[PDB]
Image (cartoon, rainbow, N blue to C red):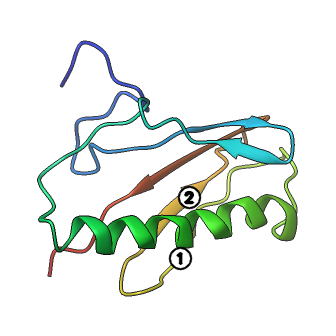
Amino acid sequence: MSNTTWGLQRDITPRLGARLVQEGNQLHYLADRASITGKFSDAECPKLDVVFPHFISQIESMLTTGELNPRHAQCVTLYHNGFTCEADTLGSCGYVYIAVYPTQR
């Protein structure tokens, strides 16, 4: 638990989130608006940093290709490079809450 938390107020297993704000045909990702958990070595930091744009490169398209339309919530589970990110619109208008949880095993 924490007094102030950027993403949704959750301290369960997925205690890390990354809610993006809608604006124009692109989404603004603010580094100062997130939290870090655990620790990534110098050999894991660069390798993970290059994987980040891969997953985001798809989100920017999901709203277009997946046809964005505030109507109802729809949970989708993607899988790439062994890593799996979860995304959902929650049926919210002009808002998409997303979260990443790297596989341990």
Residue occupying image coordinates x 79% and y 58% = 63
Residue occupying image coordinates x 86% and y 63% = 64
- Looking at the image, residue 82 lies above or below residue 104: below
- Looking at the image, residue 68 lies above or below residue 41: above
Crowd class of label 1 (few under 14; some 14 to 19; many from 20; radius 10 Å): few
**Mark carried by residue 78:** 1
- Looking at the image, residue 81 lies above or below residue 95: below
Real-space CA distance between mark 2 and mark 1, rounded to the nearest whole angstrom: 8 Å
Q: Amino acid at mark 2?
A: Ala
Locate residue 8, reporting x and y percent.
43, 31
Q: Which residue is mark 2?
A: 87
Residue occupying image coordinates x 30% and y 69% = 46
Badge 2 element: strand
Locate residue 69, reporting x and y percent.
88, 50
**Mark carried by residue 42:** none
Locate residue 86, reporting x and y percent.
49, 63
Q: Is 86 on the left or on the right of 20, as rendered?
A: left
The first of marks 2 and 1 along the sequence is 1
Q: Is 89 on the left or on the right of 3, as rendered?
A: right
| Nearest to the observer: residue 54 or residue 19 | 54
Residue situated furthest bottom in the rendering = 81
Residue occupying image coordinates x 31% and y 62% = 101
Image quadrant assignment for residue 42: bottom left
